[PDB]
């Protein structure tokens, strides 16, 4: 079965690490960071990895029941699954599918319905994924809210993410840290079942990222968010399940107005892209440009320089 | 070129009328209302209709610049396109792409950034789509917020939707009205360029709806939300652009565990589904079930009762 990537343009696609559109293609050096995101991870033959699931809108959402921490505006959420069943911590995954894969303060809204009468409520909420109480793999996360008495126990509650925050009285853009994984089971625990770190291995190459800007809700957050694969590529490979004929799919990025190739890149079968470039660079592309799979090559193929 | 629908299950797909997952399938008689949604509208050969666009996360999202209404907590948003290009009110669409297609009060968050130093601001906001100031076709909508002084003008501002509210009456579940389109031009003009109203037209048939429950943020809202096509079907048809060989595609809903067909349905070329059933019915389906296109059929095809 022939392998393909979708014909959607970059701007027609969605970040796989937060529920926002893609904006641009970006390449840069990894530096002293290890790049190991857990959302937006899928092999080219359609095996989901890490915490990756298929829904573009369920990324960084949470569902469950909540309990008030007395005297505070904090609430503890006992996690349910995406369809309100019990969360199974025995599954060999790092954390529930769709769990945030970076350390930062994600602001959004906690909503709840009382099942007996259909009454509803909603409050500003922030989840700090570097917090000691961020333990999604154990089935519990804590939210800071703007209420101390308007959430009920034993009622379905959902967190919808909006954006990120930063304490402006502290060093600007010091958080989020997009390449720092949470400790999914809390302090002094060790993450397990992670999708692997990715890095270029060939001279002159860098990762190519699909970049968005997360909305900021307060302060001076670092809003950059790089994913390794658009969410639509995850969905496409999962359905197509085309076998990989080598370890590297050569893609050409084409301007359809001219038919001319802008650049070429390697889509590694384990689900990430490299390009021949060094340094930080926002790629200049026509907005109707698209990726086209052209041929299977090896790890020693030399790309045309970006 | 062979037509296909995605192999994703119901719970693996997304509502095309609000950025939330699908939950279930529902059928019922629909002479009580006009079924004319404008999001989630697409022909089987990939022509987008109404206000439909491709992004699951831009449904009920607004982008533009905001201006404060003095002496109130209200802000007017002068709308941009979803990629920040100008919105052209003379384009032959009913309203900006992704505009909500029901009368109701949608709560979310308005966010913006100052590029000069990266400061960010976020505030609770509600848009009442039945209000006289809901005039997206003219290029503006009005938000009720929790602030009077904390938004810059002339600055890109985003509304992220979260859920719906009910207020202004002791009566329960009388809003949203999911089958009542807003007046996209307000009182200045009637709605134009609408995707067609849909109805069963074969004896014994009813529409099949792809149903979610919208988050409720206050009061006693009617949270049911039915779409005619999953958002992933819209994206699939857009890319595949497979020609329709008749006006009616026969789909079978298959349990891949057993291989057995649970029911069959008609996917009409103009982009909606019917089943042979009389009465309101919540379909009971295996969670791994999915739709499979089997053949193009003529106008005289009698579906097996579901
Ligand atoms: C039904 C209740 O709704 C919310 O509270 C309401 C407020 O949001 C506001 O609409 C006003 C209306 O006068 O008062 C409240 O009724 C929830 O916060 C509350 O928990 C109930 O579910």
Image (tube, coloured by chain):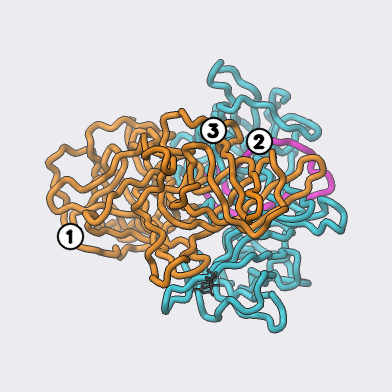
Chain colours: A cyan, B orange
Image quarter of the C terminus of chain A: top right
* B72 inside magenta stretch: no
Q: Are marks 3 and 1 on the same chain?
A: yes
User: Where is mark 1, residue-wise?
Assistant: B278
Q: Which mark is residue B62?
A: none
Q: Is residue A50 visible?
A: no
Residue lying furthest top: A258
Q: Earlier in the sequence, mark 3 or mark 1?
A: 3
Calculate the distance from the C-alpha at mark 3 to the C-alpha at mark 2: 21 Å
Q: How many numbered discs sit on the rendered protein?
A: 3
| Nearer the camera: disc 3 or disc 1 | 3
Q: Residue at x 75, y 68 (%)?
A: A131
Residue B7 % position (x, y): 39, 48
Calculate the distance from the C-alpha at mark 3 to the C-alpha at mark 1: 43 Å
Q: Are marks 1 and 2 on the same chain?
A: no
* Element type at mark 2: strand
- Name the subunit of mark 2: A
Q: For mark 1, does the 10 Å Cα neighbourhood hold few (<14), some (14 to 19), or many (20 or more) residues?
A: some
Q: Name the residue nearer the viewer: A6 or A47.
A: A6
* A47 inside magenta stretch: yes
Residue A165 % position (x, y): 74, 57
Q: Would you say B273 lies left or right of B178 here?
A: left
* Element type at mark 1: loop
- Name the subunit of mark 1: B
User: Where is mark 3, residue-wise?
Assistant: B87
Answer with the quarter of the image where residue B279 lies: bottom left
User: Where is mark 2, residue-wise?
Assistant: A24
Numbered range of the magenta stretch? A21-49
Residue A77 % position (x, y): 61, 74
Image quarter of the N terminus of chain A: top left
């Amino acid at each position: 079965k022939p392998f393909t990537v979708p014909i959607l343009t970059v701007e027609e696609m969605t970040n796989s690490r937060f529920p926002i559109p893609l904006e641009k293609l970006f390449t840069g050096p990894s530096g002293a960071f290890v790049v190991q995101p857990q959302n937006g991870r899928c092999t080219t033959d359609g095996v989901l990895l890490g915490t990756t699931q298929l829904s573009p809108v369920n990324i960084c959402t949470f569902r469950g029941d909540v309990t008030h921490i007395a005297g505070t505006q904090e609430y503890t959420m006992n996690l349910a699954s995406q369809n309100w069943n019990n969360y199974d911590p025995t599954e060999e995954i790092p954390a529930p599918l769709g769990t945030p894969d970076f350390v930062g303060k994600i602001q959004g809204v906690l909503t709840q319905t009382t099942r007996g009468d259909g009454s509803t409520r909603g409050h500003k909420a922030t989840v700090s994924t570097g917090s000691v109480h961020f333990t999604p793999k154990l089935g519990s996360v804590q939210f800071s809210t703007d209420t101390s008495n308007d959430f009920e126990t034993g009622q379905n509650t959902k967190f919808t993410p909006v954006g990120v925050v930063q304490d402006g009285s502290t060093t600007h853009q010091n958080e989020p840290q997009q390449w720092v994984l949470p400790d999914y089971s809390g302090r002094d625990s060790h993450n397990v079942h992670l999708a692997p770190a990715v890095a270029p291995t060939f001279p002159g190459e860098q990762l190519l990222f699909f970049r968005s800007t997360m909305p900021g809700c307060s302060g001076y957050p670092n809003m950059n968010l790089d994913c390794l694969l658009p969410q639509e590529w995850v969905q496409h490979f999962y359905q197509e399940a085309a076998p990989a004929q080598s370890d590297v799919a050569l893609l050409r990025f084409v301007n359809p107005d001219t038919g001319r190739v802008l650049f070429e890149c390697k889509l590694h079968k384990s689900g990430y892209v490299t390009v021949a470039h060094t340094g930080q660079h926002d790629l200049v592309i026509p907005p109707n440009g698209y990726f086209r799979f052209d041929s299977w090559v090896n790890q020693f193929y030399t790309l045309a320089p970006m």
